[PDB]
Image (cartoon, each protein chain N blue to C red):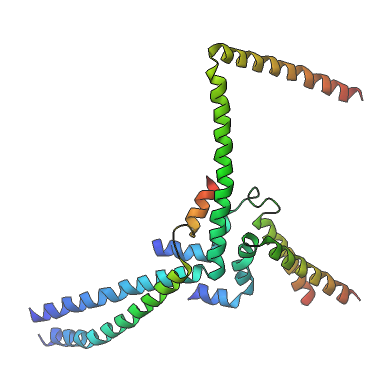
Length: 106
Length: 48
Length: 56
Length: 50
């Protein structure tokens, strides 16, 4: 019983040693990964990404607000949107053919 | 495996894969690295 | 009993060396911890956060 | 222990450690360093061409 007790106490003492060695390797790799310059550079990356993305969802929010303001008018204006989209698609189809024929003639 | 990933992160990707050409529009970091490789290869050829 | 006694006596000799190395490695852990805390480490400076921000 | 030794031995990797550092803190510094190294390469090319 004393033999097994000393065996298990040795295992309990030894397991923490390699656990803390694992902790040392993780902490030392984390320390060597980011130096003094790299921490401030990554903070500037956080600032730059925030400054860009605060413009980005602002642009998408403005676009969605414009779409909602068009949707306020009603389904008749939605039919007008579809009709003018079809008319402008046909219009650009004729315009591109005219431009291509003008380029061919030159 | 988490420590293996942490080992990989420092070795090849220290914020390098977090950049594009739209952010910092002038020239992107892979283009700077390619220009550095070309210039340093020219310098190494001239030195040898 | 003699074989197991030799084993546990080797382990009981290893107790003191393991404890001393544990104290040295704990001091190394605290040194690495203060090295990390001097620069102010968090999840924002990691690769994952910047890559996630670039991807969104 | 292999990767730390290769990092210590290779100055190119240690300058890759500061590529994005000088690209994303003060881009003028990285631009000046790149232009200085390019002009050094051109000067060496002119010197060995003569």
